[PDB]
Image (tube, rainbow, N blue to C red):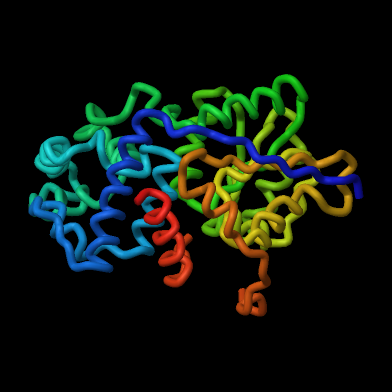
Length: 309
């Protein structure tokens, strides 16, 4: 088995991401001061936000902001969904009845990219609200990915596996790869077990498909992808065993080339803390057929808080 090599590629928060990240860090501050002194936000909207805020979902929001703005609702602002909600009723599944404060409440909890896909599934009423300015390209991790993919695919003429812990990220990447004119296949935990083979075979047979995008949990499916010798970890796991398992879809018996593995890490972000503190372990439910636990989330929130103030 030829050697594997792991690398870190640092990314920056673009302007849109910086704004989103800073908002979350502000909530972290307001939450952390409540947690230890009882101080509440004098602004009404900010105070009520804390009732549903925990270390778990704040750490989750910071992780998503390190990945992609379209994991959040900002383009489809309150004024925007109000018009889409009034608008969607004219669709047949909804013409008989859609309560308006019901569809709009549903929309208020969706992300910009989910709302984009909603407009792409009900065009006759919402197509005018679709994203059509390459907003899925606007992320520091996509900037980094586009550079790395050009090296692998154009300069090296090789294939690559891309892993993410977030199916929402995989959805966004599908539009990114289409914009970049790279053919791809996809296999995640929702893929029917029988349907896996057709996808894999296609990957092996078609030299013009450079990219396979997968959930990191597919690292555990015992699939063999040695026709690729590059692996991109779009977002790392807090358990390094998972990212090693993912990389070993390529780095395994039958592989004839050295395998190069690159983990994308946003600088000045929680991803740096996760890289430092990740701990290698085996699972207890291994005998059975990404939210971090409370203690871990508490520790990450504390570190972020201490390094600010």
